[PDB]
Image 1 (cartoon, rainbow, N blue to C red):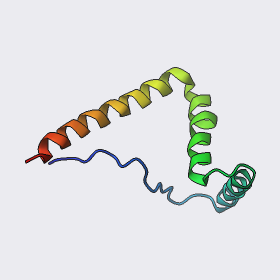
Image 2: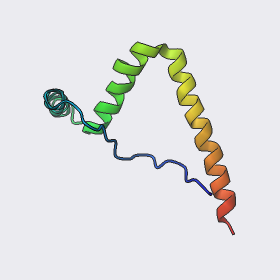
Image 3: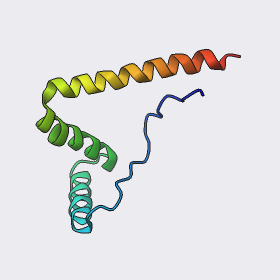
Length: 86
């Protein structure tokens, strides 16, 4: 069963999330993207990884997780490339 590597980007879904905070967050994004010219999903990803993961996990465990992913993805891509020229 030949798993694809992840696409660069995809939709992220948070189920059953508080509406008040949804509104808070969409407001913040809209402001930040108005002040900045940058896409929402970019402001958000970046906020997620500095303000949330980096703050709580520290730079080391973050780099290790990222590395682990980069690794998995590289294997998947190699397995997928070999599977597919035939």
